Length: 373
Length: 171
Ligand SMILES: [Sr+2]
Ligand SMILES: [Sr+2]
Ligand SMILES: [Sr+2]
Ligand SMILES: [Sr+2]
Ligand SMILES: [Sr+2]
Ligand SMILES: [Sr+2]
Ligand SMILES: [Sr+2]
Ligand SMILES: [Sr+2]
Ligand SMILES: [Sr+2]
Ligand SMILES: [Sr+2]
Ligand SMILES: [Sr+2]
Image (cartoon, rainbow over all chains, first blue to last red; front, top):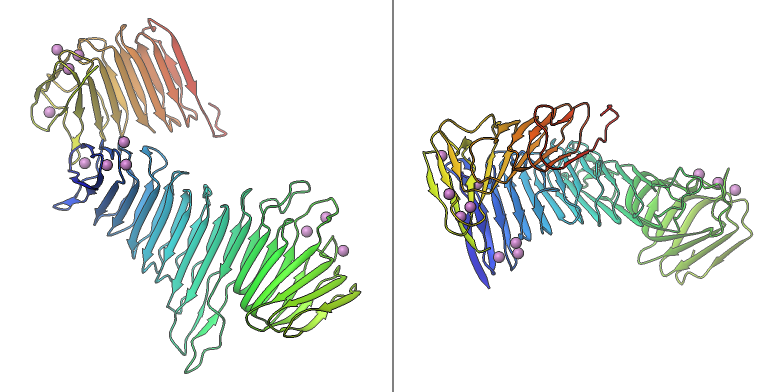
């Protein structure tokens, strides 16, 4: 049931909503902000919203402001947003911060889903921390960077979308922590131009079980063709350097990639698609000899120009069984390097081509792929 | 207790009298200007009444000519330092709560007033409290800043000090 609209003032407000769905409006009055020192907002029962909008940059939650009972907080500025809602804000489950052509530096409470939406980001940087589920939705990015969890990891999942239609190389994307991470890049430069996409670094924490990093497929620029180069990808389990602590990242998905590396003692499955350069797979640095030594490569329309390498096998304990499952569209791996592999199984319903392989310890290759290998 | 009214002070000279019930006096800011101002007169009346004094500017004293009576609890929050002595005047006050972040506190409470000084990110700023009935100091983010209770007048009741430091700078 529709409730009331409650406009804040340039003074200290004490506003309590109804038992219904209310909208708290923290706009401007003649250019002056109305979310101001000492404001106390209580949504009451129902699904309540606070819309905080002002032309001037948002620089902080003001002194003495308390917000309770409001389920959604929308923050829109005509300039940058710098905001920490990890204190004074009870009951918020959705925090949405919105800029265009300006930076965002946002820290949310661990129970607040954060969505940072930036248009025309260009050379401005976006940094978000805290939150439950964290979502970054960035368009018109050029050299500006995208950083999640450098100070405090998301309690839930992380989803980053960065779009660049310039020829200026996309600023680096870094994510630290989260239960599952997806970094999705797109390149939208015009034909007969080339754009290099952002390097991506994803460092898991104790909760990170899966990481996904996708980009626009690489291509050579021509009169009819927009050129694209894929960025590097670095994915590191939090326990990658430990001799005793078990890993957590079990699945990695790459949709087109430059020079990519994975390091996780828990890794069992890698899903690959698009245009890849190279992929090196490390399994951490545990001293104990591993018992699960099966690697599954699920490929779908994958083309690599370089090698997929088990980097652990040469001097440590690599994978002994490699399962390659081809799906939906044919794949071509330029080189497969696996110094400890003794069994290679190739399955699926789409062709798998391995142009060259270096795996001297192999004793058996068996193909069940219905299309062929 | 039964809830009463909310009484917002203004940037003009206020004369505010509460209801026989539990009232909340709000002494905030209007567009950056304090609303607790010279000559203000506050009278809580019967019931359990509270004054919330919040402003970005430092608190250095009660403004000239201000009279406060019948208000049992006073909360003081500043964006800068707090320097305040409530051991005379403010008749009927039994609880004083002072709150800063990254700024010093120098507070003297009356011998019948429970004092709670809460400082976040105290760092190198010093906290000094005197007087009071039961005295509570709750400080986080302390570094080299000191904590001094009762150097000029001892608490009439108990003293409870909590000091948290997450730096490598000796507390
Ligand atoms: Sr206000
Ligand atoms: Sr409501
Ligand atoms: Sr409420
Ligand atoms: Sr509500
Ligand atoms: Sr290793
Ligand atoms: Sr080892
Ligand atoms: Sr080996
Ligand atoms: Sr006044
Ligand atoms: Sr009263
Ligand atoms: Sr009273
Ligand atoms: Sr009175």
